[PDB]
Length: 168
Length: 167
Length: 150
Image (cartoon, rainbow over all chains, first blue to last red; front, side, top):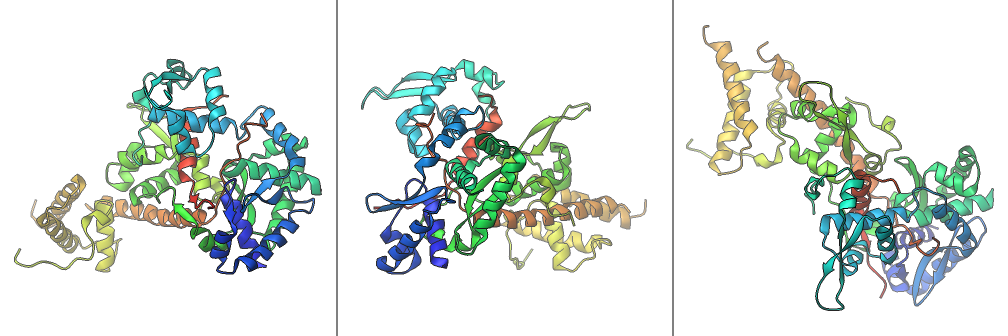
């Protein structure tokens, strides 16, 4: 089936957000009824043991997700000291701060498109980030920024010495 | 070999556009890298069926899941935000030069292009496609430029050896 | 001059003098290993002037290249190769012009493969450099956003 392959590609690219039956059917240019057959066949294929992801339905929303049986291996991935998908969430966040400080968790997660609640929490612990103030208003929203212990860690002397971003 | 490949699929899926290195994958499965590779290679074969929408590729020192190219016209229909603009010709010609001649200095680049190359170098640095790889040993101690793993990823390259040969 | 010479491209389309010269060498089927200096100089100057008329941006190197060509031409003609340097320059630049086209195709082919962003593994719960930050951020800004479900 080429329809099944397209649906897998769609749902894969959509990631954690997913897609509605309306969108999938509109993309395939077929009825929602026709599309749903395809989704079911794909969802059935991802129930074989050789597949590490499953197709779930959750609010008229379809998405691919990792199976829960594989949750401990996701633990091993992040625990075993290295370049986990966590470390990269730190860098991603830190990078947005440095080039856009003073900044607040509202403004950051707008850019990242995800709860950066945890990256920030570890960005304080390793001492690379801190408060710089608040926006004196709606919620008194904490304004984050780079420490001088961050300038050191990266071998920088000033903030001026950051590679300029012409496309931003 | 079935549960191992399910695990790698799950791991690569959760790693997304960052991918995983062979050692990272071996470390989770608690096996040798050569054993991890056999699992990955089997997984790749499974994805080659016309029936499958995603494929496992090796770009820039990591493995990652991506869609197949044939499906691109369907995926584009759902794009609101396009992401990064394609490189300017100046950036691209500067980058080709660094790709093939690294490590290389601003001067040598300007010599080949015949125009000042500060702008494109700045562009490439900010896109992490090139980095400083040292200083030359000469009067001015000029910076040397080289390419990054990000450079490999951005151009579908497993390694620099995969570059098309020079005319 | 009195007339408006016919041109497809504005000077902005070129990556400097070598690039312009390679275009002219192509347009007039010039043999690159045996360049008719006078003729090419004539074609080069006429284009530059035309663009200057339009108050366009002539980068610095175009005027330098003009003086270079006028000088090579004088030397060869007046009493008192001188162009092997320039020929070698052109052949070299041409080599990377072509290599950069091959790269451009790969950029495009790569763009057709869609990836997903990482999963948020914060629940399941570092030596880095400035490059690692720039990389993390370029990887982010490369992410295409798909329409969210309603």
